[PDB]
Amino acid sequence: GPVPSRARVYTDVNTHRPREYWDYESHVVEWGNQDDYQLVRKLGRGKYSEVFEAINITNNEKVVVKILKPVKKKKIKREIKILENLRGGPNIITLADIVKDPVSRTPALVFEHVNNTDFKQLYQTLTDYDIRFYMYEILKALDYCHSMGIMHRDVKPHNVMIDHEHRKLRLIDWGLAEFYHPGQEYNVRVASRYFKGPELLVDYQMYDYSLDMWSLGCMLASMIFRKEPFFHGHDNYDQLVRIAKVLGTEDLYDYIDKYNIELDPRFNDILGRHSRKRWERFVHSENQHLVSPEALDFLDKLLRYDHQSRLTAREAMEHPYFYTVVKD
Image (cartoon, rainbow, N blue to C red; front, side, top):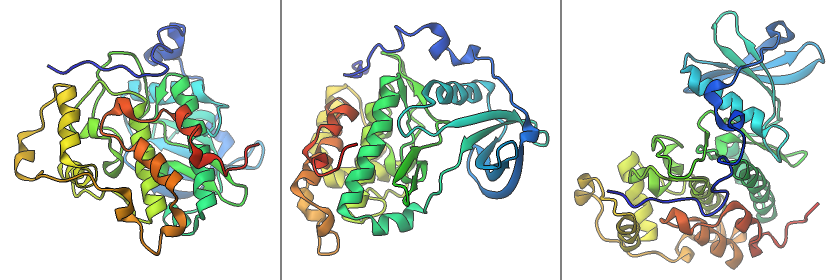
C-alpha cells in the first residue's frame, strides 16, 4: 500500500497543544442572542449555508450571517472550534457570534463584514503590484493557520474577501478546514475542482498544509496569466489531465511512483503522454505586464505534483517575488 507522508513543517503542533484545542467533538458552543441580529438581504445559498447581510442592532454594525444547512454536529463544532482557535490571526475572518436561528433550528454563524468586490471583475484590474501585495496577505493567513495546526482545504478566489479601498483581505469559509495530525488519513473530497491538488485527484489521503499551497499556485497562475481558471477540468479526471498537459506526464508518474500510488485505470484512455511546458508558453501581449522572471519562478515552486516539494507558506513569503511589496 501507499508510502506514508508527513508535513515538513508544523508537523507536531497539535500533539503538543492541550486536547481542548484540537478535540473539536467535545467543544461546548457558547450561544449568543439571536435577537441581536436583523437580516437585511440574502446574498446567496451555497452547499452548506444560506448567507445574509445583516445588522447587529446592539452597535448598528453590518455583519454577515451564515445560517447553516442541516449538517453533522461534528462538522459544525469543527468549523466553530477552528474559527475560535484562529480568531484575531492575520487576515483570518472574525467570528463575531454564534446564535440559534429560530426558523431553521440550526446554528447561524455571524462574521465581521468585508466590503468585497467580485473576484471576476477584481482580477481584471489588479496591477502586478496589487497581485504581489494580495498574495503576500493571503500567505500571512495561510502561514498563521498552518502554524496553528490547521489546513484550510478550500483556498480559492471566492473564499478570499478583499476590500480594495482599504487594501484589506480576509480568508473566509473555514467549514472544510481540518486539524493536521501526522499520519492521519483525510477525505480527498475537499477543495473546489479547479483548485484541487494532485494528491486529491490521485486519492492520496495522507496530505497536509501543502494542499493549500497548490490551491494558492492555481490562483496565482490565474491572476498573472489572466486565465480563469488556469487548470480548467470538466470533471475530477479531466482536472488531472489538464494539470498533466502543463506539468507533463513523466513527473506525474514519478510522483505516484514515489508514494507507491496507482492511477485509476480510467486514466489509461485519457491521460496520454505530455512534456512539461515552460511557463513562457502562457505569456502573451495581454498578460506580459503581470509576468516577471520572479513571478514564474515562484509559481513553478508552488505548482509541484509532489506535495512535499512545494514551498511552505513561510518559505513563499521569503521569495524574491515579494521584494517589491512595501512591508509595514
